[PDB]
Length: 276
Length: 9
Length: 98
Image 1 (tube, rainbow over the protein chains, first blue to last red):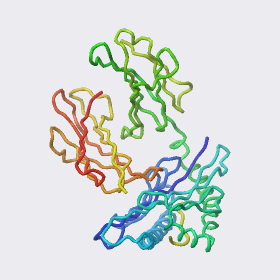
Image 2: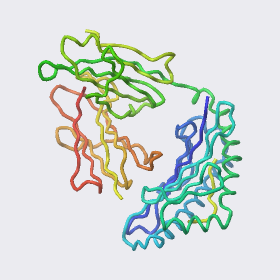
Image 3: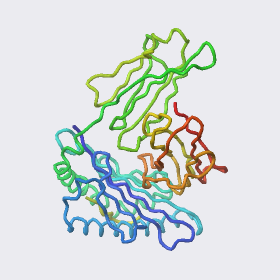
Image 4: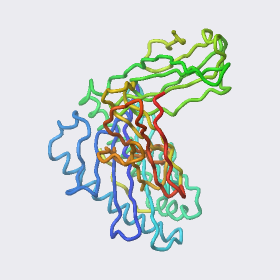
């Protein structure tokens, strides 16, 4: 029932290159829908799902200019951070930013987000009150003061409660069957004779969206983490995901082992075992 | 709809 | 500071010898975003390899999916070799069909 929008923004300086590379990716409900890249021939925001082609040229021209402004902002900030951290020239540096908003089922604002990282590390973030800032690093305190002085929190709070909600409402009405979909995991168990006396049961879940999923094993019982290996969830490359979890077992006595697959698309958790 | 940032760092 | 890449190599579909498929190399959890990813067949760079766009996770770390068309056989082996500044040497992982 819930929904979100995110812009994920990155600028990267490298030793020789005159200007940094700036990339911005927007997401509705965790699916990419727009992108800008300053390396591109003639950089602009481009649609990244078919449902975004409804927006006319005035939408794209404005978004592109916002992107060019952000790239100017990341450029100056990268420069200022260099000085804040007494870093000299000839290094590589990263600045990243995360977006704005989460709605509940009723489409009202649950939370606003605004976070920045330098060299992949928390630099500064707007707290959930959308009024105060968290900055851990001694160097970050300079930004925190400057931003407290100029009422930056108010600007970002207005975006987060206003445009971010309004435009997410609009986007959700526009791609109504493209993002109101979940694919269920089809699950199966495979068998692998391993050094004698023992064997690995591998529980597979395939073809599912979104990524969040859990695979458990029970020894007829209630729990197994003692040599339960798994893999991190992985993209298949077609928009669906894949995961397995495995458990080591006595050969012969494998018919009392049960795998459970928990996914939001399921009516109830899947249950299956090795089927010879 | 993209955010524009306020003051630089 | 550097975060070292985590690598998986796996097929998009259930592998069957003789059947066209897609081999992925999924590289996550790294920093900085500059990286080198080759896919390999029998130790040699596969020339046409698709590279999704630079993306990052909410812990700030970057990830990439690289993929290529391939036909598994009984005998050929596939791998992914990743070079990144977190690692003094490249890191290779081999496709295991299971």
